[PDB]
Image (cartoon, coloured by chain):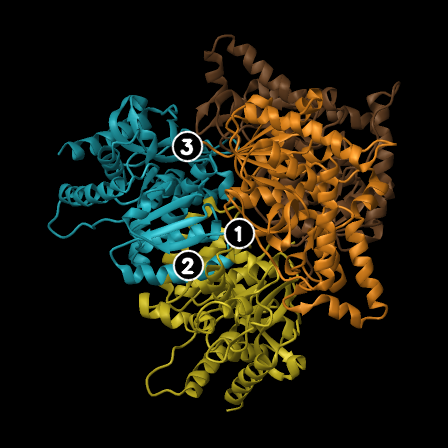
Chain colours: A brown, B orange, C cyan, D yellow
């Protein structure tokens, strides 16, 4: 009768913020933090523990090492390497593949038998890699994918239409990156057709474009302003964590393996998927219009070309 | 029929973390952030907004200016200045008093008529200053005081006795700083007398001391490890925010004005106090043993001497 | 600075269940319960108070009288009369209009200046009546409307498609009653067109029909089984209460006054509407297909005909 | 990887209220309800399901049978028989022991391997019986015990001292019944000695007595008023359910087996105990003053005498 245990690997801005989200939300009762910067870990674990008496229900937080993954239920990986000058995107992929082969190797050697949630960029490539490296079933390896992109799109639509973001149903699918796309054929508020309504406004076509540009380029915009982006990603990772531990069967946009859905295979990419205590139960195949079909196929090709090069 | 509006003044590590706590907890529906580093604000507001579609209920976040305090319900002040080399503690007090005279002045000029929650250190001095400067009733000016110290003490006791921190009732009172004290005469788990039990262990007296030292010196220890401390303070500020907006009549340890309680007057200092939608309803005067009476009086004197110098 | 105060008028199965929901959810910190059956109230208030120590945040519960509405924020009306044999619907309407004239009058005389949430059936008629009797702006008088019918439709769809109910976006609009209608033109899971998908199944048209019939006739089915229905209603009333007190600007299907929307006027009826701390901020006018336009107009006509009588 | 599954056996006012609490709180994602009154169950399950779309997170509710316990995590027993005229307490005990032997037997035969939470009165006796009949470790059989009596005591103290109930630390221990006792040596608000403070008030000894009498006799008072008590019990059962499923290591007053603690053995009785995902981790032995030691020993003797018969 063990409790719910998350191990976070990588304690930078995103991981540390996700850890604080867990302490606020009490999704699980045990959080273990692993990072090579063991002084930052020790300092963060103290600071987080001191918050926990005001957590809704008990959360225990500790510094850990790979062996602590033995009975972990979810391993969340935020660790990795940024692109350097003169490095090609292929170089950046190769560099993080080497890191992930090592991390996933150490996790599996602990006898871990839970679910992976990968957040490191490029997330769709690294989720695919974690699946291959770990030998686990596809249900048990999840990339965060477009979980945050979809939230950014909903946030911006909720400002354009002045309603709660929870009342906006809107999705970004595809690569978490340059090749993502908005699903305007479905974006709505209680049935209100948002793109059609925006097209009625003056320069409405320009507004539609700017809503998507601001979604696509959100990280770049936050980094220019404050140097790093982390709250939005932490909250999205908490949302997935919730769906798993509360066994929700909730449809979320995450990076999932396709084996025929959307006429694509052997690729991880952002799509709506049903999430529950066993991970991704199934990918949801929704209708796409011509423009969306075109863009989604191009995104998948982009991801598959990159991996093939590697 | 207006909603619940918090304005945060000061968007460093503590303020930004408190803002993220609010986005996780949905205590209030509107958060406004004010800081002279307007680029950091703009970047944080974007990053926070992107989390809000997964907030439990709607939270709107925006960058603001003093005029936005006009209809704010709670103004939370984290802004201030750290001590510099060659500066005496008196110098550090004088420097933050000048900043607070300015901030409080601008807030009041907006026609603000809500509650202040002060977090800037030295918090008991600056809460007293905010009370004087604002002209408001003492109920409506609250320092965070020992809200975090008490949580640190409970956290450490919950580790020593291996139970949920929510099942540990333990308090730190006095100055948030060197002169704080533990209330061992009351610290218990369901009636278990913790100090008495610790005294039964081998070198039990040394354990009692180390539990308090680690509480008192927690910030110093976190700063040596990761350079700054912020999660624990953010969570404590969220806890007070909750008691106010949910009208709880909850007893929390905060910095409150004494006008006769504990035989002290004309001083703000950390004590248990009943918190509700009108701020501090009353200070709770609990029995203190001789050692606690001695230490609390010395803490109050320390704070009053400092203010008198200023 | 006052806290958040709800007064419940009518402590039957629905109202008492709604009170328990409030004790579980801690949406507000004060609940006052008013009912002519003062012994049942005294009992419920004790039993409820004993739960409050485990409520997420403080909830104070007490037995009250009309004067306690003076500074209430939300007054929730579940009180009324059921239809008797040899009574027409018109008779049933008239009887409750008399009760509401009395209740709303006593509430207003207390100096109440908050929001009404009407739950008593026929809820669209009685919401309209409460608006008229109270003289308050339409924003501050809300009927529960199809808040539960919509949840029932989502529940049944969540079973037919095996997914979280929270991941089903689907709505019932119109009269809370015989003339309500499903908005199949909109009902979807992350963009999956539910009616279209059901029509691909064998006897799929029969399944579509049965999902709606089971939604429409849910209360009848529950009453036949256990003699009364109340948990669904209580939870829907708690959801509206949450949107108000947390100032959400959440779109919910409630009974709202139309003044031109959907080409209808001078009628309360179930529609998506933005709810916040001020009550109904605005009705949302969604596109309706031919079938839905037809059924919605018929529902509104039905309600206006009966009120005109 | 399985989700969290509770099976409720006994769908009376207490069990149905507990089910509604679970729908409000989303502590677990699956609830199965078993009762011989299968029409009431069918009705409650429909009404409850219709609330679930507004639950914080997915809650699936269904009508079930004993075989559904096979992979349940928690089985909550509210079923039983009330005392009849001309029946002694011993008769009442014997009748429920027969019912429990049957229920626990059918549960165990399903392959259930989780935790029992017994709520049926007399709860300390029936918790002990369930431990014996099930052959499970003591950690995995929990009676509700004084979970509600403690909340009642805190509620009344919160009224006498005008503060949040969550800020009152106070406990009732012993038999859930006539021999329960207040732990005044501990009861406090942030260190304020409540009994001492009450004794300073005029007729303060009378107030102290009345706070306890109203705690002890609460169910009687509620039954006299509205004929049954259920909200308090449901919320206490939900609080224990929360501590298990969120693995809290929370100290709660429940009915636990003593094997030496408080100098008592071979008896279940209400005591503070650490609760986590494994059930009762350990009983907490708190210091008791002379009066409390006397009353606690008497309560345990009362329970052991009746079981020995």
C173 over B167 or under it: above or below: above
What is the quadrant of the C terminus of chain A in the image?
top right
Q: Are marks 2 and 1 in contact (CB under 8 Å)?
A: no
> The disc numbered 2 marks a residue on which chain?
C
Front-lying residue, B16 or A223: B16
Mark 1 to mark 3 CA distance (whole Å): 25 Å
Query: Which percent across, then down, holds residue D103?
Result: 49, 74
SS at circle 1: loop
- Residue placed farthest to the left in the image? C86
Q: Residue at x 70, y 20 (%)?
A: B39
Residue pictured at 48% horizontal, 49% vertical: C25
Give the number of callouts: 3
Image quarter (top left, top right, bottom left or bottom right) of the N terminus of chain A: bottom right
The residue to which callout 1 is attached is C56
Q: Which residue is more in the foreground, B184 or B289?
A: B289
Helix, strand or loop for disc 2: helix
Q: Which mark is residue C48?
A: 2
Other-residue count near label 2 (Cα within 10 Å), few / some / many at <14 / 14–19 / ≥20: many
Nearest the camera: D258 or D195?
Answer: D195
Q: Are marks 1 and 3 in contact (CB under 8 Å)?
A: no
- Judged from this view, the residue extending furthest toward the top is A203
Q: Which mark is residue A61?
A: none
Residue D46 shown left or right of residue D274 in the figure: left
Q: Is residue B103 above or below residue B249?
A: above
Task: Please identify, in this view, whether the residue under mark 1 or under mark 3 is nearer the observer.
Answer: 3
- Visible residue check, residue A173: no
The residue that label 3 is drawn on is B1
Q: Chain of mark 1?
A: C
Distance, label 3 to label 2, CA atoms, is 28 Å
């Amino acid at each position: 009768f063990k409790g719910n245990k998350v191990v976070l690997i990588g304690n930078g801005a995103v991981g540390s913020s996700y850890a604080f989200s867990l302490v606020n939300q009490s999704i699980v009762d045990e959080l273990v933090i692993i990072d090579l910067d063991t002084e930052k870990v020790r300092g963060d674990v103290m600071d987080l523990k001191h918050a926990t008496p005001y957590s809704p229900t008990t959360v225990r937080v500790k510094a850990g090492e790979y062996s602590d993954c033995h009975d972990a239920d979810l391993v969340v990986i935020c660790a990795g390497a940024a692109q350097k000058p003169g490095e090609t995107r292929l170089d950046l992929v190769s560099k993080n593949l080497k890191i992930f082969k090592s991390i996933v190797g150490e996790v599996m050697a602990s006898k871990f038998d839970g679910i992976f949630l990968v957040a490191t960029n490029p997330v769709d490539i690294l989720a695919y890699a974690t699946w291959k490296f770990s030998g686990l079933p596809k249900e048990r390896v999840i990339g965060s994918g477009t979980i945050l992109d979809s939230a950014r799109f909903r946030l911006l639509l909720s400002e354009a239409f002045d309603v709660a973001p929870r009342s906006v149903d809107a999705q970004i699918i595809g690569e978490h990156g340059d090749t993502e796309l908005p699903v305007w054929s479905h974006a709505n508020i209680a049935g209100q057709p948002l793109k059609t309504l925006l097209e009625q406004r003056p320069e409405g076509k320009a507004q539609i474009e700017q809503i998507f540009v601001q979604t696509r380029d959100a990280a770049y915009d936050i980094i220019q302003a404050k140097g790093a982006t982390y709250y939005g990603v932490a909250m999205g990772l908490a949302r997935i964590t919730e769906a798993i531990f509360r066994n929700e069967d909730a449809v979320l946009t995450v990076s999932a393996l396709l084996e025929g859905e959307y006429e694509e295979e052997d690729v991880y990419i952002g799509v709506p998927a049903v999430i529950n205590r066993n991970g991704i139960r199934n990918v949801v195949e929704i209708p796409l219009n011509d423009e969306e079909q075109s863009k989604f196929a191009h995104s998948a090709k982009t991801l598959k070309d990159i991996m093939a090069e590697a």
